[PDB]
Image (cartoon, grey):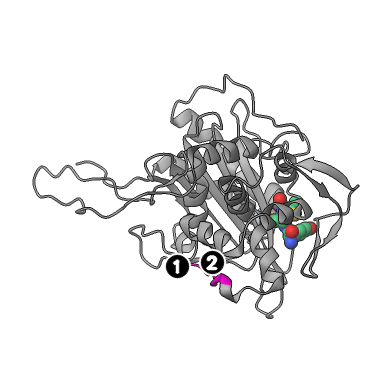
Amino acid sequence: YQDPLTINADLQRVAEESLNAAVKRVGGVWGSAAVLEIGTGRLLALAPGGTRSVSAIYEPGSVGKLVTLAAAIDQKKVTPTSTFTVSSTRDMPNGERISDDSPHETQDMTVAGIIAHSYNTGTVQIGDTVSDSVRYEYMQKFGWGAKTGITLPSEESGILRPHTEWGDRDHYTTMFGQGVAVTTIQLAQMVAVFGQKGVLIPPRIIDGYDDENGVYTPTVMGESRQVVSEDTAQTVLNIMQGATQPGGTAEGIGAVKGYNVAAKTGTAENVGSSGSLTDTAATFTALIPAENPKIAVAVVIYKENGTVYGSTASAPVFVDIAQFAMREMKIPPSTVPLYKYPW
Ligand SMILES: CC1(C)S[C@H]([C@@H](C=O)NC(=O)[C@H](N)c2ccc(O)cc2)N[C@H]1C(=O)O
């Protein structure tokens, strides 16, 4: 007997424990977390025990900025040190007003720092350097709007409306993960690209089988794709290491002692039972150790009639999971510094 599934039992336990505790700590309704082994697509942990991580869809928020960032970089429209002006609000060519989470002093900042702070006013300028059809194409390549094809029941495909349907609001909201709906597994599969030299590897819960007596491992199916170039992947991976740097959205709370973390936070309004934007999903997508990623993690906590933030709600779950996984996988602490671009 060989265990044919990919789940790590102890990691799964840590995942469920942390997630349950955080959903309660924060007064959420539910949560989800997915842990992928980098390079293999092997699913190390999936919480909760339902098919929630596979069937629940929500607007992911600013974790979706990674797609926008990767599109602009891959199309060679901006570099990590390209500067844009950030301000409390910004009025766009099309008449839309974009605002940052909280008012702050107007300043110039690099692309790297814009992502670290997650300034929407800076992000929309990064996104405007590329057309809607191109961004939409990168969204599909990243796996949005499609089932990941994992062999579990009830997987949802999510909602990615054709860009031909995007109005003036959508043009911008889709840049920061609003006006699209994803699953937690889609989030993990997506962030893993940046630790896989731009390659998306479809997630798997079933290893092979021995096939010594009876060939039971699937013929063919699978297939990974190059979403983004190797250089684009490395660059986003470098930029993501700004998350736990001072001023980064994940500072302190997303840090895993002794390991370099690459991360993005998100906080997105979601539609409540009432039919209005009463709810929020707090998201966190991460890669660790950043210098040479071994796992990709996505966490969502959902709260009805309230605000939860990716950093304060979801990052602590990532931390508990990542801390165990590094021991469990016997990964030594980071010997190189956390990457920093000028901001
Ligand atoms: C709260 C933020 C710093 S703003 C920005 C964006 C994407 O998630 N979120 C929003 O613009 C969202 N509409 C929102 C929700 C509640 C807020 O207080 C502010 C912004 N990234 C966030 C993050 O990193 O968690």
Who's the residue at 48% across and 38% down the image?
Answer: 230
Q: Is 4 situated left or right of 41 in this image?
A: left
Evaluate whether residue 14 shows in this view: no
Asked whether residue 108 is drawn in magenta, I would say: no
In the rendering, at what x and y percent does residue 325 appear? 49, 35
Q: Secondary structure at mark 1?
A: loop
Instruction: Name the quarter where the C terminus is drawn.
Output: top right
Relative vertical location of residue 22 with respect to residue 157 in this rendering, above or below: above
Towards the viewer: 139 or 157:
139
Who's the residue at 53% across and 70% down the image?
Answer: 159
In the rendering, at what x and y percent does residue 173 appear? 68, 64
Name the residue type under label 2: Ile
Q: Is mark 1 within 8 Å of ligand 1?
A: no
- The answer for how far apart the CA atoms under marks 1 and 2 are is 7 Å
Who's the residue at 47% across and 43% down the image?
Answer: 198
Quadrant location, ligand no. 1: bottom right
Name the residue type under label 1: Glu
- Residue extent of the magenta highlight: 157-163
Mark before the other along the chain sequence, 1 or 2: 2
Kindly check if marks 1 and 2 are in contact, taking CB atoms under 8 A apart as contact: yes
Q: Residue furthest right?
A: 105
Residue 57 shows which numbered tag?
2
Residue ID for mark 1: 156
Residue 122 shows which numbered tag?
none
